[PDB]
Image 1: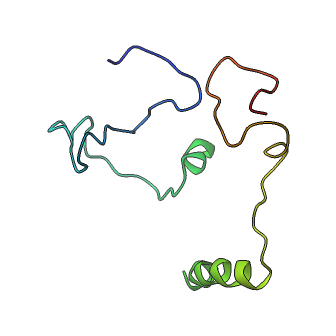
Image 2: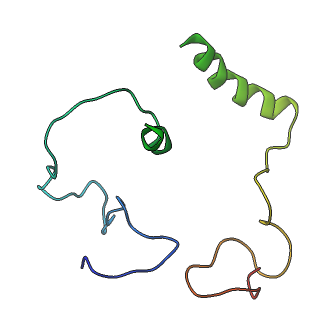
Length: 48
Length: 48
């Protein structure tokens, strides 16, 4: 549900498209609002 | 910002003039069945 693996085509943000798209959970919050320097790739943030 | 903007119109111009643009690194080509069927725990061909 969580709690499973399948290397190559792992889910990190991918969500169900169901029978019709534009479906999403109400839990759009998983974080706190915080800001920092500009980063436009994941690897750029990893350098700092 | 303009150099990055000239980049958006560089790629969509160059690739039509030069043609090509099926490029990456190492293996992605040749031997048996087409496209990226793997997916975990398979090594050495039968999609290939």
